[PDB]
Image: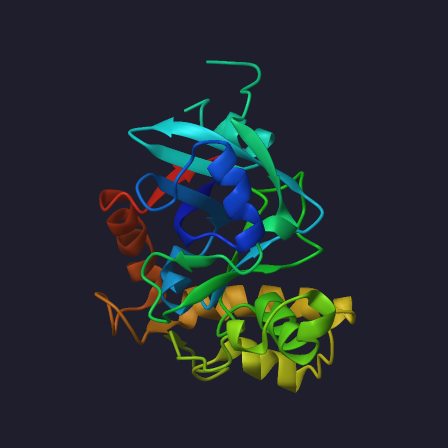
Length: 246
């Protein structure tokens, strides 16, 4: 049970431009979406970027009405069982080629977003594209911090990584930016101490859902427990997201 977030690709990175050009696809007219799976549609307000893996060869698929989806074959295969055994993508594109593309992420209050790398993004789970909410996701916060620290090493620009984080969810136990708090209280120094992070992912999901209050959006002031299904429905209604299982 996942929610597939349609992240609109607005301007493609220079080396991708050639490929799209050579394959007759144009990002300015057609809608080209990176599809990222999430279990927390209520946190979509706090998106600061978008994650893809440099090591994954993504497919570009035709979804109809001039919509195109960038994901993995296996991810797309699911989005259709709701009648083929295999769907040939129009062409494939490596993750590295997409880094630095500008994007518009649904509901995100942060502007001028970009596609950034994360090497540990799986090919066998979800869509190959990952959501980034550093305020409420410890994993995201830690990866963000790394990219900010070693931009040359990861092949990005320091400006691309948004470091001003606006609070989305208030919690009793952890305050307004629970990922920041949990990374700090549990002394998570890097994305390498994997014990404290797996513990942190759990605690953040629990308090966020059960003791969380929205600080932003249509349902500002509501318990997350109540707001979550309502925010989900809105995005689906607005054609910004859709349901997808495995």
